[PDB]
Length: 223
Ligand SMILES: NC(=[NH2+])c1ccc2[nH]c(-c3cc([C@@H](CC(=O)[O-])C(=O)[O-])cc(-c4ccccc4F)c3[O-])nc2c1
Ligand SMILES: [Ca+2]
Ligand SMILES: [Cl-]
Image 1 (cartoon, rainbow, N blue to C red):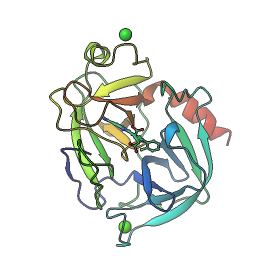
Image 2: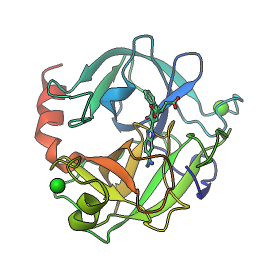
Image 3: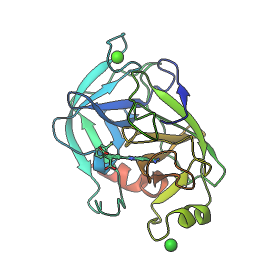
């Protein structure tokens, strides 16, 4: 997160860190055994880390659970990043409490102007790499589809939306990938891609979760 603030320990209880010996992507807990992340964050050997604040210190509240299976959307296109969503099933269910809680899936898609909370342990520099120890947060609005397509002509599909600031300075970045975009308590997006981080007129592009609720529900129900 570039231009964000320190969230405060466990104030984002649904945030998870996907770890393979180091933090590589974020994710969201949607029930006690499933996490939603981005398809491009897929790899084998993933350990899901819940209740984290400082990812380099065991401070208490952490629960490290291995992933039993990762299900990348069947129509994921690694070249366009269209359908950049993945479900991870945990080996054991997590103990939910105030520090570890799931977030609700939406019933409707959000409108432009909706203010959302984006969080993660991704890079904090737009020019260079600085990775934080604790979780960073950024409040950002969903942009209109016309502004989004104007910024990324020919690269936005109906399964994507832009959120952020066209002036640059505040954005999500590499490492935040897979994590949550929550608006009015519902998970509306997944950090997917963007051109650099916090560059003028190049907002972040997110996977539009409201277009995948039936898929998520059907897939969880059959696995
Ligand atoms: N501007 C934004 N709002 C934004 C949002 C998500 C991003 N995710 C990434 C991202 C970038 C990389 C670099 C890799 C490098 O320079 O070392 C790249 O390929 O350009 C990699 C990943 C990535 C790829 C696979 C797994 C985990 C990852 F974070 C990104 O998500 N950039 C991002 C930028
Ligand atoms: Ca920790
Ligand atoms: Cl277009």
